Image (cartoon, rainbow, N blue to C red; front, side):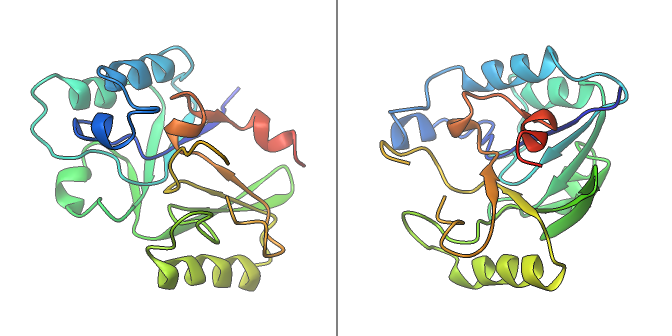
Length: 186
């Protein structure tokens, strides 16, 4: 039945990221991402995008129109590059500006774009602290986030009694994460 998927940091149209993360990003990554979502989503599913959706809204290659066409419910948890909520409103059914809490088969899940701690560079320490704060305050069991890109080594959201999983495309071979992998923890 209804499955939950999580993906983030798609950077649709961020052509330059091919240069910035030569390692993982390659020309035509939008098509690859959209493809992997295509062969998985069903009308009753729900896809969570945890940040940095599109680089701009000039849908010259149909990437956005295609995304819009995909089946299932789509909700977004805003990342630092996600600024125009009005432009976004028609690519998502629900938009949460910072976090969203959901409960799955008992356990409580915090959805945010920011991690508890960036294992590399803590560019947004204040936002990281808020995530931790919420996590603790709401007695959350897991944190699903994005923001931290692929690197040649390996979240820091472990130095705190916090469990997490990085939904960033660069870490999951441009595939959404199923609610299955969540259960692999529970």
